Structures are given as C-alpha cells and as structure tokens.
Amino acid sequence: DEDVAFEYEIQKTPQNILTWKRYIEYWKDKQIRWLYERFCSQFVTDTSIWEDYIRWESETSRIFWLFQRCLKSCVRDCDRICLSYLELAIEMIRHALASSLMKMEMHRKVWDPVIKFVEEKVESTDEAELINVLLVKGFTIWSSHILERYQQKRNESLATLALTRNITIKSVYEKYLLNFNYLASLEKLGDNQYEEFMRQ
Amino acid sequence: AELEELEEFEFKHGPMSLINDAMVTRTPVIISLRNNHKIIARVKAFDRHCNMVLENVKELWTEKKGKNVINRERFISKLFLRGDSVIVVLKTP
Amino acid sequence: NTLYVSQLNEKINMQRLRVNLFLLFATFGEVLKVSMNFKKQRGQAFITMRTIDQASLAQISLNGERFFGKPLKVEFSKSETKTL
Amino acid sequence: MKFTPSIVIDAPQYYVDHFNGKYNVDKCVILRDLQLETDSESMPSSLKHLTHILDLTNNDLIMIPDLSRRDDIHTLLLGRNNIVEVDGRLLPMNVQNLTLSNNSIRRFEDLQRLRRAPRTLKNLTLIGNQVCHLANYREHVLRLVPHLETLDFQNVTAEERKSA
Amino acid sequence: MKLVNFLKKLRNEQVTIELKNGTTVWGTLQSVSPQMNAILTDVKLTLPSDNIASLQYINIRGNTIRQIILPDSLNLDSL
Amino acid sequence: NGIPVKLLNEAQGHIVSLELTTGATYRGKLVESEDSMNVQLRDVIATEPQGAVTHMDQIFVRGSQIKFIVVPDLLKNAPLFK
Amino acid sequence: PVNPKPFLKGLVNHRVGVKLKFNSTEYRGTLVSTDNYFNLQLNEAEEFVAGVSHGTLGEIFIRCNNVLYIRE
Amino acid sequence: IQVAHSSRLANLIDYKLRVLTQDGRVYIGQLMAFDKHMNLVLNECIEERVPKIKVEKRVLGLTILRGEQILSTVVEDKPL
Amino acid sequence: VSTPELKKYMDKKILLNINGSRKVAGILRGYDIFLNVVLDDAMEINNHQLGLQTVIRGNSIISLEALDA
RNA sequence: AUUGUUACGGACGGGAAGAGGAGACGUCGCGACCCUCGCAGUCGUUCUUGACUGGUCGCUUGAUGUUUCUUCUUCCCGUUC
C-alpha cells in the first residue's frame, strides 16, 4: 500500500513537517486524521499543527476534544486559543471561558466580550450560552470571576447584574470601597436592615 | 446614475422586450448557435448583453463526419449562455 | 570557471554541437552556458560551469577525448565569462 | 541516501537549463553526488514537471528507471553511474538525448533491451562503457538500434548501416 | 445591471465550459474578473466523444467561454 | 498604459518579424509604433505558408489581425521595466 | 434625406426580410421594435432556409451582429 | 508539473507558460509583461503546428503576443 | 484616437491585399483614425477594371504594399 | 541612538518486396569534397567609438504546414485476446 511508503518517509528523516503534510494533505480523510494526530503525538507540539488538527477534526464532542488537545502544550498562542475556547463555550460558554483563561491568563477586550454574553443572557446559541452559565454556576459565579479578572467599574456592574440574575455586584463594590460597602449591605438585605446597610 | 438608470427600461420597449417577458413568466424558447446547434430551455435571468441564465436545457447538435446526420442529446440545467453565440430566441405558446 | 575548447568537428551543426557539449559536461558539474557566443564553430566553444572544481575536473579528464572524429583540446580561459 | 519524495521536493528546480525546455531537476540535496544506490524510486513525486534534463549523474544507480508521459525526460543525463541494464516501457518516446557516459554495460546482450528498437525504444544513444570495447560493437548497435543517430559523439552513417 | 456580477459572486465551485474547440472542461472558478478572465485549478481536457488528455492548472480568457455550468442550483443577483 | 506598447515604441529601428491570421511571416525594420499596434516596415521579406515567397520594399500592417510581433534579445530587462 | 435609423423606425409594424452569414437562412416577419445597437424583434416569423421553410415560429427576436441586411 | 496556488496575473509574472491560439497552434514562453487585453510578452517563442495526430516545431520569434486570438495560457515550469 | 502615420504614403500607388484572397490596388487620397482608406483607384485580379474610386472599410484592410518607396 | 475584494488461431502498428500516392510554395535537420581559423564577426571615421548580422551543395529514399487531383498479395518484428 501507499501508507507503508509514507510511514517509511516519516521514519527515515524529519523534513520540517513535510512528511506530515504528505500523509495528511494528500489523503484529506480517516487515514489523514490517523496520520496527522499520530505525528502530533510523536514530535511537534506547535500551535499551527494543533490548529490544523482541530480543523481536521471539525461533532461537538470532537470539537471539545480538539480544544483540549490544543490546550495541552500551548505557550506562544495562548491568548488566541482562549478566544477559541470562549467561542466554543458560547456555542459550555462559562466553562470554555474558564478553560481559555487557564490556558493564557492583554485579555481585557476578551473579558469584556465574555461579560457582554452575561448581559445578553440577563435560539440554539442562546441555549448554549444558558448551559455555559449553568456550568459556571455549578463550578462556583463564573461571570463574576471573569469580571473580577478584567472599565473596572463597568466590570463590577456586569458582575452585579450577573449576581442579580446583584448581590455579587454589591459585594464587589463593597470590596472596592464606605458607600460601596453600604451598597453591598443593601444588596445583601435585598427591609429596615437593608435600609440601614444602605445608609451605612 | 441616470445615464445607466434610464437604460434599465430600454429592455422592455425595444427588441429585448419579448425576452424580458419570457424571463418574467418562465416558458420554453428555441435558442440557435453558430456551428450547427439547436438548444431548448426556459428563461430565468437576463442582462444588457444577452448573457442569459435558463433551466431544463435540452441540447441538439451534430458531430457526424461524412455527411450523416446524427442527433445526439443530453440534459443540462442552469447555464450561463454568453450573448456572442446567441442568434435567435423566441417565446413559444 | 570557463573552459575554452579547440580542435573539433566543424561539419556538425551549431545547436546539435551545443547539445552534445552539454551532454558531455553534465557528468563533471552543472553547465551554466546554454548556447555558444562566438558562432564561428570548428572547435572554439566556451563551456561555462558553476563550480571551478568541476571545470578543473573536466579539463583533467576530457583532454584529447574523441568527440565527432577528432580529439578535443581542452584548456582554461584567459578572461572570465560575461555570465560569471 | 535512498531516492524518496521528500528529497525530490527539496531539490533545486529553479535554474532552468536554457539549451532546451525548462526545469532542469537535480533530485535530493544535489543529484550530482546524491548517491542513490537503489533504482530511481518515487518518480511520481516529480509528476512530469518539465527537453527536461533530469541530470541524475555521479550516482550509484543499478538500472535506469522512468515513469512519465511522452514529453517528460528528453535530455536525461545519467553520467558516471553503474547502469547494468536499462529495460523499460514507461519512457518510450521521450528519452532521445541519453547521456549514459561511464556506465557498467558489459555485454552486447545487455543492450538487447535497447535492441529491437523499432517500437521498444523510440530513441537511445549509450556510450563510454565496457560494451564499446567489444568486437563489432558499433556495427551491432547500428543493426539493432537504428534510432541511435549519434553513437558516442560520432554519427551512424549510411555506409555503416549498410555494413551492419 | 450586468450578469458578470453574478459570476463574480461565485467562488470555489466546479463548472463545465464548452470552448470554441469543443471540450467539456470542469474546473474551479477562482478570482473571476469583469472581463470574464477565469482560472481553473483542476481540469479535464481533449486536444484537437471526449478523449482524455488532461492538465492540472490553466488560465482562461473571457472571449472563449460561451457557456458555464454547475456553480450551484440557485438564482440570486441583486444586492 | 500598456507595457507591451511601450516596449514596441522603444524598439524603433530594429529587425522585427511578424505573423498575421493567414500566417504570412514577414521580417524587416520597424518604422513607427502607436497605442493601437500599427506597424510599418522597410526592405521587408515575405515567406507565406502557400509557397510563393517574395521580397517587398515597404508594407503597413493593421493591428487587430496580427497574431504576434517578434522582438530581438537586447531589450529584455532594461531600460523599459524599472 | 432618408437616414438609416429613421428608415428603420418607419419600417416598424410592417413586413421585414433579414438574412445571416453563418447558416444562410432568410427570416420573414412583421417588425415590432428596435434599439440603439440595431437588434430586431419580429412577429409571424417564417424561417426560410434558402426558399424552403423549416416552420412557422411566431413571435421572435434577433441579435444585430449576425444580421446581413433589412429588406421588404 | 509543479505550480503553486496562484491568485492573479500579477503574482505569476516571469514564468514559462504555454499559450494556445484560435487556429490551434501551441506556443511556449516566459511571461515578461502584462496589459489590459493580456498581450503577454513571451521571452522565447517555440511555435508548434498540428495539421487538420502529431505536433511540429519552429524557432523564429521572441515575441510580443497579441490578445485577440489567444484561447487560454497554461503554466509549464518555474524558472531558477 | 491616435492617427495612423499615412501621410508618408500620400500620392503613392499601393498594392493592397484584403481579407479573403483579393488583391485590390489604388492610389491614396485620404485616411482616418479608423483606417477607412479613401483611395482613388480599383483594378481586380488576369487584370480588369471595375469602377474608378473606392472607399474601403477599416476592418477589411490587412496588408498594403507601397509601389513607390 | 503597499496587496486583494466590493460598490459608484484472430485483430492493430511499423519495415521490406511484387502487382494495378503525386506535383508546387515555403519552414528546421543527417553527410560534405566545402567555406571559414579562433575565449568571448564585418565596416565607417579618428587616437577610441556609431551602424549592420552556421552560409552553400547532396539526402544515395531527413522532418514538417498550405494547396489541387485520384488498393491487394507475401515475409519479418512488437502489443492484445
């Protein structure tokens, strides 16, 4: 067969991702998948390679697996990856975001975007988002964390909103802070006690 | 704008009017060509220079050497026939 | 780099001769010169090579080699070529 | 090393041989001193890119291997090789200008693949081997390979043909 | 206004075209121009029934292409 | 503007061969060049595909029906490109 | 005095005769309308292939580039 | 035959291209220049005839090709 | 737009060779940008005369040898 | 300290022989009794610069595009069933 030859080529000497290309790009499909993945496992732990693998894989489960693989060994293009994770989450959103963060902790815009999903939440896509939120909550919750990580005032507000969907926001405000503390107290209360807290 | 815009209604008044009508209300038409050809199809789109798009394209031509007539046929659909080759088109009842 | 040939068969045609030369000189190294510049024939041909070593080798080996009846007199060029 | 696809890919196909055609390929890092001990395998990697002038000289090629269409390797240079026998049905019409100098063609019967040349090989030269030293070798060549115009730089004349 | 516009919008799709010589040649459209200067990536040829004598790449001029086929079965032009 | 046209203009006073739709291959001097590819020649030979070759004093050729126009090897890189 | 386009205009809603170079066939029908590029549209069209008719077509359209002439 | 995924006429300048004409005579040559009508200046023209079986050869021109009668150019092999 | 240089060929007899194997001949009187050559003679090919002056269309004038250099 | 896109046994082929494909026009090749004599050709004019560029004869059955007219038998060599 033609596979044996390919294998031999791969073995004899490394040609700077040439053998891999020969294996995968000529076939691609199953065979190609088998090849490229194997190659990845063997030697190269590059970002581009990972991306390629992911593309090849591209169902939801498969995508997730690909993402996981990418996450395993990825130093240079971490921020970029994080975006991908976030996207995946949106389509396990909160979870995805968390994963992205873990991969590459620069990332203010991304954080803001993530928050805005929370705001929106407060059809399939929507469902996915909801699921992600739920996951985050379970983990905790996630949105709040993201906000904290992340303009600051805006983030705080977002967190508060998420909590309401408010208490969390109040807490954050208090932490930041006397007025803030009072606000937090009020949120917590949310009658006389609440009023008192607000006053404080 | 107006120099090109006034040319839009020039199809429906002049010799393209019939073809426009055909396009509007899809009906079969007999299309001839240069090197011994007869095509039959129904109209769908239209432009300035007779570059038409059709449906249910039945082709009838000859590839017979030595003066023997052979009518070969094959179904084509959703073409893009350029205006330089189109000679005669006509709306049949 | 260049090697000035001499004492060869003038009766053979130009293009053909050039081709023959190319065929001959491919064993030593990469022949840079595609066609002859003089256009006089009768031995006078400058075989331009990429490497000097290759040229040297050619000079060594093909000195008085049978090419179209007569023995070719190999020798190093006086001036450097326009391409080199 | 062995003639693989990767090697072929690597090869410098930039500087075209300006005598005829285009793309004078030199397989591996350099076909001149590549040291291809086995037969020319993985010929499909080139895929009939380009006279072509696939200069595979200064190698250790045991047998001449081809795999392409009628216009793919006219000016093939296999100089200073160990060519024992070069029988094949792939390169029928293409290979006219065959530079097979300093080969290991021993017997006249070894050239029987090239012989019966009316259909077997449309053109072929061959020279500078052990078979050239044999008695009545040129004549034999003339008899068998009529398509051989230039026999070791000197042409196959009418008189010669008559003699053979 | 024009139906070259339609052609322009199509990208990465196989289409047969019968030339003045008379060959059915399926290929990808690539960067289509306002002058109909097509470019095909993979193609099947018949040099003067269709005999197989195919080459890979080719650059087409717009004056030759009289008919085009199989972009995709859908009609949309105005935007 | 057209680079080929420019090239043609540059090559004024050079031996330029020609070929038409019918295939009549000429070879002589170039007199003048324009935006439309209108060529005029001097001391122009004529070797047609039919057989009856001739030697003509002058000729003018219409641009639309020319198949190709020959140029020598001198004006290749300089001084037209950059 | 009498120019071409005005003549053409005049000849509307009247019999017209037209011929082609490639596949010489005389088309006979009554003219409908024309444009700046001299394309044609006929009614009651009879496709006379060198005298003998192929079939009565009816309402037809003709491109300019092929047309040889316009007659009665 | 090796040729990379080129986009437009500008990216494929200075390459050995085949060219086909209306009558059916095959050409070869390196593409030097560009124009509105694709009047592609060939570096060296080896024209080929096929009678109305087998292809012939010529070697007269190093031509400026005109764009009226060209059918479709084809890439042969890259230089250098 | 650009005028063809036919002022050189004024008042000189020209042996034309138009499309479709027809050798017409006549002296040049007037010219233009479209190449509609207004010439004042017409003798067809052996030889016989058919009308004096003849204005010709630009598309159907391929080759034109000047008799007087 | 610019680039891109959009809008305005039977068959087939080749070679040879016998019996009832040929002539023109050019365009590139195998031989040479010829020419010509060398490392990057000829001449005008002035102490260094401007112009112009493999030829001829056989083929003793070399290749090839227009353009007019009108196959059978035998042997040898390859492919296929």
Image: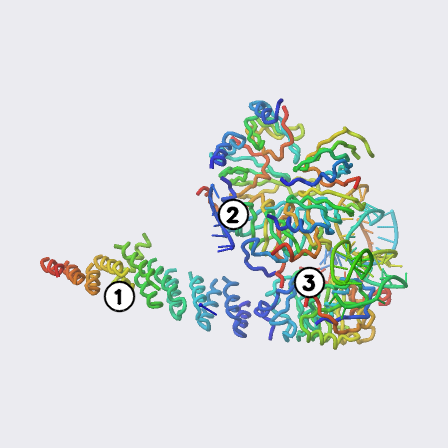
How many other residues sit within 10 Å of disc 2, few (<14), some (14-19) or many (≥20)? some
Do the residues indicated by labels 1 and 2 lie within the same chain of the protein?
no
Which amino acid, by three-letter code, is at mark 2? Answer: Leu
Whether I5 is drawn above or below J44: the answer is: above
| Disc assigned to residue E70 | 2
Residue G13 point in image, percent of width and height = 55, 23
Tell me the subunit letter for badge 3: D
Q: Pointer 2 indicates a residue of which chain?
A: E
Q: Which residue is mark 1?
A: A139
For mark 2, give the secondary structure. loop
The reply to whether residue H54 is in sight is no
- Rendered position, F74 above or below B17: below
Q: How many numbered callouts?
A: 3
Residue mark closest to the camera, 1 vs 3 = 3
Residue F51 at x, y = what percent?
80, 46
Residues packed near mark 1 inside 10 Å, few (<14), some (14 to 19) or many (20 plus): few
Q: Amino acid at mark 1?
A: Phe
Which of pointers 3 and 2 indicates the residue nearer the eye?
3
Q: Residue D53, image x and y in percent?
A: 68, 65
Q: Is residue A17 visible?
A: yes
Q: Are marks 3 and 2 in contact (CB under 8 Å)?
A: no
**Which residue is most to the bottom?**
C60
Crowding around mark 3 (Cα neighbors within 10 Å: few <14, some 14 to 19, many 20+) is: some
Q: Residue drawn 73% across and 54% down?
A: H60
Q: Quadrant where the N terminus of chain A lies?
A: bottom right
Q: Which residue is mark 3?
A: D18
Three-letter code for the amino acid on which mark 3 is drawn: His
